[PDB]
Length: 154
Image 1 (tube, one colour):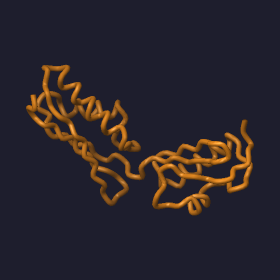
Image 2 (cartoon, rainbow, N blue to C red):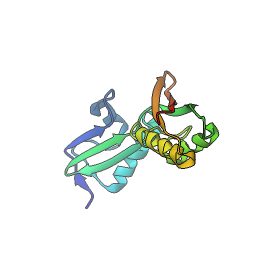
Image 3 (spheres, rainbow, N blue to C red):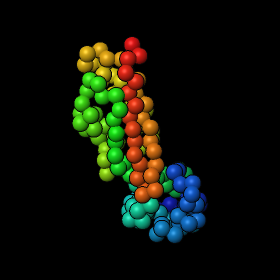
Image 4 (cartoon, helix red, strand yellow):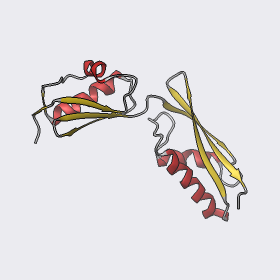
């Protein structure tokens, strides 16, 4: 069910760049007939523009919506409160959970990392620590994120 005439293009992640400016990076326009091939083509175009870390184009009725992933890349993950589990272990643990160095970052998987590391501590020696992941943006289109472990809440 493709090759349909789109009426409007929307962006689920764009706030600085507007859809009119974003349209210039898209091979398709308003009123155009778009296939799933055009969905992948718009994806790869916006991927090749390099401003977004990930590009998803999907349809909703006659509306084409492009959700994009956070511009900054994970540059460094720093750990504070590694009293039980090794920081090197936490590094790969985060990487295997989604947030990996050099990879597109998700602010929404941050909470899952917090809960996961909290659970991991409890699983070892029954260590009760509170984990908070603080994401700090730096002017190089990357983020430095610090993992705060509170030592001894229970």
